[PDB]
Image 1 (tube, rainbow, N blue to C red):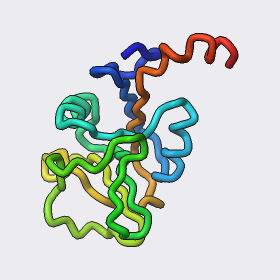
Image 2: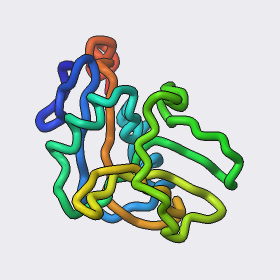
Image 3: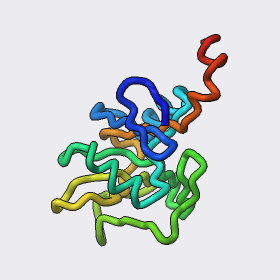
Image 4: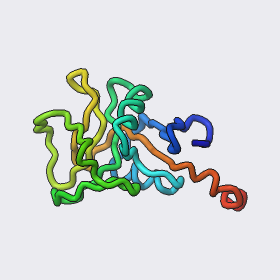
Length: 142
């Protein structure tokens, strides 16, 4: 909720969109170190509000990880797989195989989850919890 500079405060979380080129592995790697995680869509509002900050052309990595077509859809954050909230793009062929990580892509003029090889580089969203309250002496040291 309280976050540095341009982190979009929403509810209790903060979401920062990046248009740089990173793999899902590197985006998870560059995130988390900031106390944040990749864009983990907890609510349909998380989605519908973040796509207002996202550019209608880039594809932004989400925190949904599967690591071998295991069926282990988990958000790298804490958020479990939302059974009521699965926003697939469509019956999308793409190229997804092996490791599969969903991104928010604007295609067919619709924002939706598109799962792509996590070794692919694309844009990303980083989400940090309102942990700034805990970072009082923490960041005072750091």
